[PDB]
Image (cartoon, rainbow over all chains, first blue to last red; front, side, top):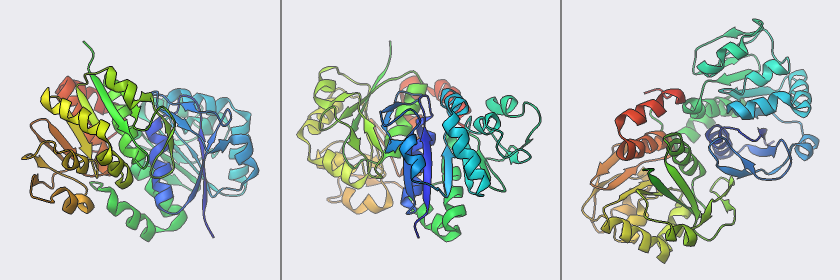
Length: 188
Length: 188
C-alpha cells in the first residue's frame, strides 16, 4: 500500500532540485529510489555536491512501476536526460499507464525531447522557456507549480518545496501534505 | 581574495539544510569545503540521502581559517556535532578570531554544548527551543533568520534559502546576494 517514486539522477543535475523532493517525499512515507542514469556510481551535481544513488537506473527500471517519475533540473543534467534512450522508455511507459510525471526548472525540456505530454500546460525556468516551446507543442504557464493532467512542472530551485509538496498531495492527498509541511517552517 | 566556507557534515544531518547553503554559497563564488566529521567516507543524512564530503574534518581543519563555519541541523546530526571535541576546537577558534558562525534548525544546540556565543540572540527550530534555552545563556528569537554579532541562526529546512543568502550577504555583500537570488525563483 506504499507509493513509490523514481528520481533519475544524472551528472550536472541541480542538487537542490534533487534533494528537496527526495527528502520531502520520504517525510511523506513515499518509498523513493534515487537512480543514477549512468550506473550506481556517485554523481557530481551542478554545484559539485556528490550524491550516491540508491541504484542504477537499469536495476531500478526492473522494480517498477512507479507512481511518480521525477526529473530534476540543471541545464547539463536535463541534457543528459534528454539524450538517454532509457529515459525515453521509462517516460513513455509512465505516460501509457497514466502515471504521474514531474519535472522542475530545465527538467521539463526532457519531456519535449521524448515527445511526452504534448498539448499540456507546462512551466519551466524562464531561461528554458524558448527551448521548451520549440514547435509550440505545449502551452506555457508562469505559475510556480503547474499541473495539467499527469504532467506536473515547476520553475526553479526556489520552487522546489512547492513542487515536492504538490507531488505529495497528488499521491497521498492534501492532509498528508499539510502534516509534512508544518515542521518545515515554510513561509506560505 | 576568495572567501571560504566550512560545512561540517555528520551522520544524521538534514540533507536539505546541507545542500542548499553549499549550492547557494558556490553560486556566490565562495570556496566551500564540505567536511565529514568522521572522515572522508560518504555520509548518510537524516532522510537517507548519501553525500560524499570533499574532505575529512581533520584535513579541512589544517587548511583554515574559514570566513564562515556552517552547522547544518538534523536532530542526530546536531547531537554528533555537540559531542565532537574537534568541533569544539574549530568553533572556539572561530569565535576568537571573530569569524562568522552559522547554524540552522537543531544546529544551534551545538553552540550551547560548546559554550559558544553566550549572550547572543539566537533562533532554532521550535522543537529545539527548550534545549537551546537550558540555563538561559541566550536570548530567544522567533525570526526566520537571526544575526547577532558573529552568530547567525535560522529555524528550519524551509528557511534554508534565507539562511544561505544571509551568509552570502555577510561575506560578499548585498549586491552579490541579490544577483545570486534572482535566478533561483524565490517567492520573496
